[PDB]
Amino acid sequence: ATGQDRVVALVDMDCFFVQVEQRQNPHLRNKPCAVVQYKSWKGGGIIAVSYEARAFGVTRSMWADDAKKLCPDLLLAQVRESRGKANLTKYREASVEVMEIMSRFAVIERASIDEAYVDLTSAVQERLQKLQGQPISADLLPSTYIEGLPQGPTVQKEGMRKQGLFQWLDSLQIDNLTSPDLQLTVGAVIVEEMRAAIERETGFQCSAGISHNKVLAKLACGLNKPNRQTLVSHGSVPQLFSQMPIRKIRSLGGKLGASVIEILGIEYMGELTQFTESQLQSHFGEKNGSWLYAMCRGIEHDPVKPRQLPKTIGCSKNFPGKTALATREQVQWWLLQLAQELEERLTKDRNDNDRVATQLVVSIRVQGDKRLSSLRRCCALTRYDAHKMSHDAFTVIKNCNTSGIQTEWSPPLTMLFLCATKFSAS
DNA sequence: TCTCACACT
DNA sequence: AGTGTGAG
Ligand SMILES: O=c1[nH]c(=O)n([C@H]2C[C@H](O)[C@@H](COP(=O)(O)OP(=O)(O)OP(=O)(O)O)O2)cc1F
Ligand SMILES: [Ca+2]
Image (cartoon, rainbow, N blue to C red):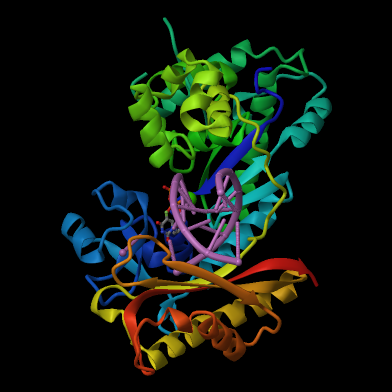
């Protein structure tokens, strides 16, 4: 079993937030520019960077003042602030523009505000039968790269792409409606169409990866960016993985990937193939070891889940440094701010998508603790009312106040989080 | 520099 | 139910 059953794509909207601001403000298009939140602290934190700006070294998580040192003509759009906090509504609404188009072509799993996986297996099958048995023209794939091609016995990027595509298509056995390579190729044609539709109907450009599973689709998408798509076939996997750092594969970018590297003494994904499955399991657990054994051979079975809507709706703000909440009524006022945005977003959700959430998650962080969350508590969510929700959130966290004073809050709070969960049909 | 999904327990 | 990981 070679992990070639499915055709799966990952589509990534290139520097999406920037694109959203560039569509709305044409003065920004085709310039180095970035999206920031909170202008006051060091010019604001950069959450999205156009490709022109990235060429100067500007990255996400940079302060805008720092990015301006690297890129003096950098243009900035600020995120909308509402009730003292960054509000992402405009981007969420652009994201829904895009997913609704993608869903006309295939079933899509929303992976984040700017990317979606796409299961094209069924769509490919139908296109294959309408195609009589007729060859696939290079003209159907005007922005597609075939990973690992050209090879064997031109100095410009587009010349390379074409030569690789020619070599791919010249050897395609179109007379076999079950070759996985043919299916990928038809998958790629559909994604060219889907990306043409997204750009025509929204003005947004994006990159896509096309392969046999989600991890490879995602890896492929990042290989030829921006506004390009890449086909990673099963056959390309041994050479692709032979120099591919372990941390580049989805879910190995963190502690597990680090311990795979250290315990095993390897650097690249393909070095995993010399270990038995039992060996991998003993070091990393039954699930992880099984997952690694198959993955380093290009095989992964995680399904594209037919889910175009988030499972949770969440509202958080950080209060770092001297800005940590120290008084009771301060903590109340911000919970109320969080509860109010949440109500706004919950009501739109109940009306657009026919469902109500039923559980409220409250999470806080205390100054001096180490981790994203210090403590997580839940309670019932019965009415979309901001005042009750914030009253309830306070109720389930007021005992964390180690201060004996009634009006003070120690240790001061460095993060407040309200999340609606456990949706049911409405 | 605010999100969202999921595995373990 | 609560914590921790991984990612955008
Ligand atoms: O830390 C983050 N903060 C943060 O707001 N977002 C938001 C803002 C951003 O446009 C969007 C994109 O996430 P991506 O990691 O996929 O990167 P892009 O900007 O779209 O460009 P590309 O995929 O490299 O071409 O999510 C992602 C984060 F990772
Ligand atoms: Ca993106």
